[PDB]
Image (spheres, coloured by chain):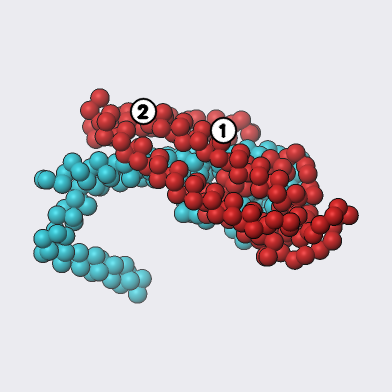
Chain colours: A cyan, B red
């Protein structure tokens, strides 16, 4: 069943062949094919930034879950959704979560309300985690996305004739 | 540990040197370097607008927390997140929060449900706070962001050859 569901995606994508017939849509699809160079540049740039921000935030928070599937989720998945307006402030900002004792390790700890945000996170320098979130949103949600729009606009005008 | 986490960010950023080898990615990175003039203009314009809107909203609400770390959060941090779809309407709109008596100061007061939104805020002219939010979203989320896209598009086309 699982592979068939993915197989349905391939069949549905084949439907794009219809628009090649139309005079005003055929050129559009060809231009779309030529945008892959711009998309790959954005993905590689985004991938580097996600790794840098994701690991640093995970390293600063020090969640006590420390599980490989969960660590990958907090490093890659959670920052990725922050690009699309999903910002779980209650899972990184210590001021939004109650303080509690969870581990015998020295320092202070806070208990996030999220299910996959870890049992408890460190609060040594949480202003930096907030600051990193501020910088990440500026670079990803604004600088990178607007850069891709400019790259798309230039490419569309250049390859329109060909 | 804290500085090492930031140090990891610097090491990861160095990875962008790889794309300089590729023929179709090397020029892209150079153009990115030349976009800093546009970014600085947007940041300075945004910084002025955040200060203007942030302080006025804080001044109108008159939250009773009145703590310097919290005041800075409500002046800079909260309006910044409003750009990226994080609009805590229950923390400024009085109609969304219950009315209660918190201080002996004359007037009427309401109790926000937020943890860092202040113990209670004034409700003298709350329609203006809502109106300021409407104007802020128009200028920031629409006018400034779309302006930066246009500035990026013009710069990308101009410096492509060089």
**Quarter of the image with the N terminus of chain A in it:** bottom left
Mark 1, residue position: B6
Q: SS for tag 2?
A: helix
What residue is shown at x 52% (from left), y 38% (from top)?
Answer: B46
**Residue A61 appears in the picture as rendered:** no
Relative vertical location of residue B60 with respect to residue B15 in this rendering, above or below: below
Q: Say whether disc 1 or disc 2 marks the residue closer to the N-terminus.
A: 1
Q: Any mark on residue B34, and which? A: 2
Nearest to the observer: residue B33 or residue B75:
B75
On the rendered structure, is A155 left or right of A94?
left
Residue B150, horizontal then vertical, whole percent? 35, 41
What residue is shown at x 75% (from left), y 49% (from top)?
Answer: B62
Q: SS for tag 1?
A: helix
**Quarter of the image with the C terminus of chain A in it:** top left
Q: Chain of mark 2?
A: B
Nearest to the observer: residue B15 or residue A12:
A12
How far apart marks 1 and 2 lie (CA) works out to 25 Å
Mark 1 Cα shell of 10 Å, populated few (<14), some (14-19), many (≥20): some
Residue A82, horizontal then vertical, whole percent? 50, 51
Q: Quadrant of residue B20?
A: top left
What residue is shown at x 19% (from left), y 50% (from top)?
Answer: A31
Q: Residue furthest top?
A: B162
What residue is shown at x 46% (from left), y 36% (from top)?
Answer: B42
Q: How many marks?
A: 2
Nearest to the observer: residue A99 or residue B11:
A99
Mark 2 Cα shell of 10 Å, populated few (<14), some (14-19), many (≥20): some
On the rendered structure, is A70 left or right of B59?
left
Q: Quadrant of residue A26?
A: bottom left
Q: Are marks 1 and 2 on the same chain?
A: yes
Residue A129, horizontal then vertical, whole percent? 61, 41
Q: Nearer the viewer, mark 1 or mark 2?
A: 2
Residue A7, horizontal then vertical, whole percent? 28, 69
């Amino acid at each position: 069943r699982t592979v068939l569901c993915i197989d349905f995606m391939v069949f549905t994508v084949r439907l794009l062949h219809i628009f090649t017939v139309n005079k005003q849509l055929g050129p559009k699809i060809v231009i779309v094919s030529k945008m892959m160079k711009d998309v790959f540049f954005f993905l590689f740039f985004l991938g580097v930034w996600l790794v840098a921000y994701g690991v640093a935030t995970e390293g600063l928070l020090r969640p006590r879950d420390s599980d490989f599937p969960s660590i990958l989720r907090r490093v890659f998945y959670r920052p990725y959704l922050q690009i699309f307006g999903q910002i779980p402030q209650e899972d990184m900002d210590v001021a939004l979560m109650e303080h509690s004792n969870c581990s015998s390790e020295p320092g202070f700890w806070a208990h996030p309300p999220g299910a996959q945000a870890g049992t408890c996170v460190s609060q040594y320098a949480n202003w930096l985690v907030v600051l990193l979130l501020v910088i990440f949103l500026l670079v990803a949600n604004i600088l990178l996305v607007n850069l891709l729009i400019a790259m798309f606009s230039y490419t569309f005008g250049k390859v329109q004739g060909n």
